[PDB]
Image (tube, rainbow, N blue to C red; front, side, top):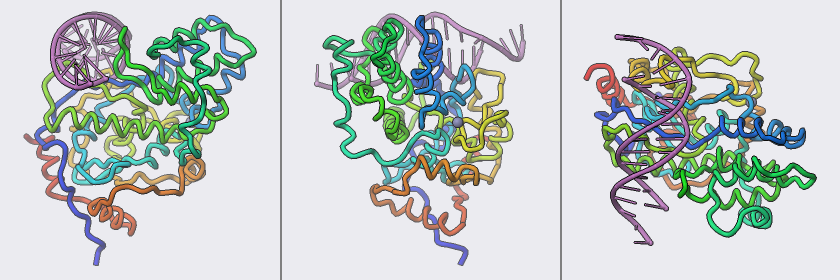
Length: 362
DNA sequence: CCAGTATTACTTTT
DNA sequence: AGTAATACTGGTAA
Ligand SMILES: [Zn+2]
């Protein structure tokens, strides 16, 4: 008995005829802008203002990222094309060369290092609207409005700028509007109220928040394409902190890691994964989907759940709950978890030959 | 030319 | 409020 049996997915969002279809994808995660805005303030940030972000239990890892961070998304898109239809709602799975790969809060935490513990009690009530009423008249608050105030505010004993800085940070990196311009969508109301309490903001599980936000963009994306990738130059926006999604395929799949990833010199070993690796420079601003598909090749070495190294065990003990949470009943995902739980790997070989045929031959 | 990014215009919902 | 079209960036390769 070589293990409990793992069932094929009920369905897939995309047929394998779409695996070669390239798309432009629009991020909404302005890591580079925020840092430039912060560094170019006419009245600079004080030590306490600076160290608030550079020693933040979650956001200090934003500073371990490479300078001028630019997102690379065809790994994420390759994953998206392989999203399985499942019952669970708090985790996503992608079937690559017939191997299911999980994107859950544990994986969002191992790559980003953000706090992914349970929300504090009655966390929505946190804050008040007093801080924002002191700077923003009645109406919509757009992201450009928060940035503008920050660059103009005068530094002073009230740490109100830091609150504006934090609000700018949250709504530009964690929970980010899609629409821009004169009619940009209003920024997340929770972040507006949460930014009034700097203590609360230093400890909140912003990873869970970022993660739950990513889950909505994933669902919206899959809803939008309805199984067909069009032929358009018009980019599709996927807002939120997508760095974990950008790296998942590379952490899971050694063939991609060997061609497109390099270790980051002098990184600390207790940091999450995004601090300790970097994308290789390529011919383009990001990898082409063809490059990903070609390097996938015929590889069978793929991790379903990406295993932590020993140096990463204290990290996860600190940023993840031991509270595996409650989700909808999933006979298929349960049968995967049961087989992986016993040390056995999963591989639907018809799906593997389909993937190989759709990329390498057709 | 390209993928990532920023911006403006047109469509759908309400 | 949502999506599509357009244009800009900083490269590479022809
Ligand atoms: Zn780090």
